[PDB]
Image 1: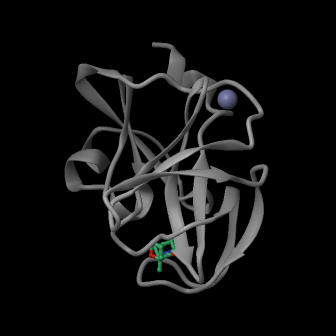
Image 2: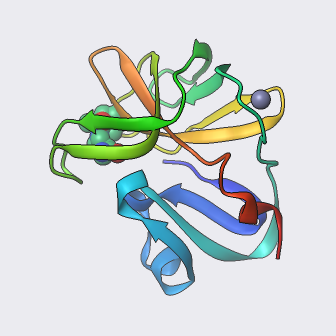
Length: 140
Ligand SMILES: C[C@]1(C(=O)N2CCC[C@H](C(N)=O)C2)CCCCO1
Ligand SMILES: [Zn+2]
């Protein structure tokens, strides 16, 4: 589990969104595994606006932050899980690292701010849903 809290937005994995998230929906995209809902309180996270390919992510199943090198956001084939059939997920970045179902939501960050959240795992790989192209998170 985990979310990004920027401005009056909460960014979560679409497959982990709660009823309150769907009842206060701003935007969702199944192909990216992302959903954004509105919040009453302002958040403290800042979004990175860069092309970094190195950063650090939080792994809840290890209670640890790991430094990683990650690929550029791309369209990647992801195997079937309890939440999605086997399909292509867009705006996904891959790295070598540990990721279980429960690690989704952990933040990946670079020197500029939050880059994305854990969305996929297994086989010694971790995949992150990028948010750096969502410029509207910084306004309204
Ligand atoms: C099985 C695993 C996973 O990769 N997925 C399940 C949850 C949905 C994920 C997706 N397609 O965005 C895929 C391993 C890592 C954490 C989440 O569960
Ligand atoms: Zn950066």
